Each structure stands twice: as structure tokens, then as C-alpha cells.
Amino acid sequence: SVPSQKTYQGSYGFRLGFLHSGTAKSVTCTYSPALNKLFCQLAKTCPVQLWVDSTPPPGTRVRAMAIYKQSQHMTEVVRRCPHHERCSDSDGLAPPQHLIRVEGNLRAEYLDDRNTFRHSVVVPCEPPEVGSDCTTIHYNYMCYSSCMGGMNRRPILTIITLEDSSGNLLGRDSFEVRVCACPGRDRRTEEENLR
Ligand SMILES: [Zn+2]
């Protein structure tokens, strides 16, 4: 099967937000609204904002999962390549096979689906810090888009779902991801191509 990628705000008005980081050659993570695509370096912090219109119930959670963007690859589980799954760069919580990690959240849980074999990482939905209007989750992507035997140059999407305590759907959003050495240059290039 294939997880849905349909944008759905739901009862709570759920959607994502991204910082405006620019495209200098030194940038480590940058988001393109025109492409709905995040460009980031290997294992670097990717701040993703969560926005809602109203407060969801206690026990609400936020899950991230990657899928291949191209239909002919959609049924294939997105996972780390044969090199990176064995490089012992564990943070003590994320399984070494998982592409997406959450940084600095001890309540993060990593799922290997018993039926689809797909990977995801899920955290409790938390209110903004005092003085802030949204909550930020810090993600890491642990393989390059180009990794042989892994993504192998195939584009992926990250799907973020807002879930109730049973795992039922409350909201959904998504964005394409390219993990690369020079996010600034590649974003500039792909945006120029689009024009
Ligand atoms: Zn890799």
C-alpha cells in the first residue's frame, strides 16, 4: 500500500511552516515555497513549524514518514542505504535504518510498521513556549538523496500527520525533500528551472 499525501487541515486547522533561510552557499537547510521542497545537508537540523487554529486534545501526536514521490517507486519503503545503516551514528533511540530522526526530544518514538514495514518517528504535540505562536520540531535526514542502494537519486516526500492517541487522522501536510551537499545552490538551480 501507499500512505495518503492529501493535504488536510482538519478540525484544528493544522499546517506546517518553514523559516526563511536564504540560498547562500553556506546555508545548511532551506525551504522553497515555489517547489514545496526542503533542501538540507546530511544530518543537519531541519526546523519545521507546526501551526494550528485551536488547541488539540491532550494525547495528540505528530508523526513524520518519508515516501518516494514517483508512483513507480511509491510501494518501496524509504530507508537508509547499505552504508549509512551501518555507520554506527546512533543517537541511542533512532534505529540505524531510519531516514528521519527527531532531534532533542526524549519522548520521540520510532515505529517499524508490523504490516507495511514502513518507518516513522512520532512525538507528542506540545504547546508553543511562552511568547511563541507555534511549535517547532527539529528533524534530521540521515542519508543523501544520491545514496547508492538507498534513495539512489529518487525524490522523496515527507508526510507529517497530526494524530489522536489511537493513531487516527486529525490533520496532514507534506513537502518534498532533497538531501544534498549544497542546498542553497540546488534550491537556486531548481527554482530557476521552474521559471
Ligand atoms: Zn546513505
Image: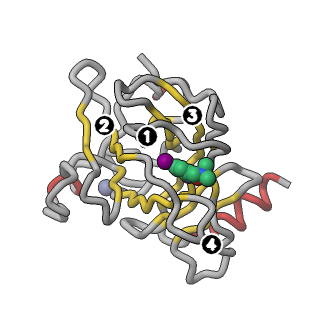
Residue 93: which quarter of the image? bottom left
Label 1, label 3: how many angstroms apart (C-alpha)?
13 Å
Q: SS class of the residue under badge 2?
A: strand
Q: What's the residue at 68%, 70% (across, down)?
A: 20
Q: Please report contact status of discs 1 and 4: CB closer than 8 Å, yes or no.
A: no
Where is mark 1, residue-wise? Answer: 66
Label 4, label 2: how many angstroms apart (C-alpha)?
28 Å
Of 134 and 82, the residue lying toward us: 134
Q: Is residue 70 above or below residue 32?
A: above
Mark closest to the chain's N terminus, 2 or 3: 2
Residue 7, visible in the rendered structure:
no
Of 40 and 189, the residue lying toward us: 40
Q: Quadrant of the C terminus?
A: bottom right
Query: In the image, which disc is placed on residue 119?
Result: 2
Where is mark 4, residue-wise? Answer: 184
Q: What's the residue at 52%, 60% (across, down)?
A: 128
Where is mark 3, residue-wise? Answer: 172
Q: Is mark 4 within 8 Å of ligand 1?
A: no
Residue 184, visible in the rendered structure:
yes
Identity of the amino acid at label 3? Arg
Identity of the amino acid at label 1? Ala
Q: Please report contact status of discs 2 and 1: CB closer than 8 Å, yes or no.
A: yes
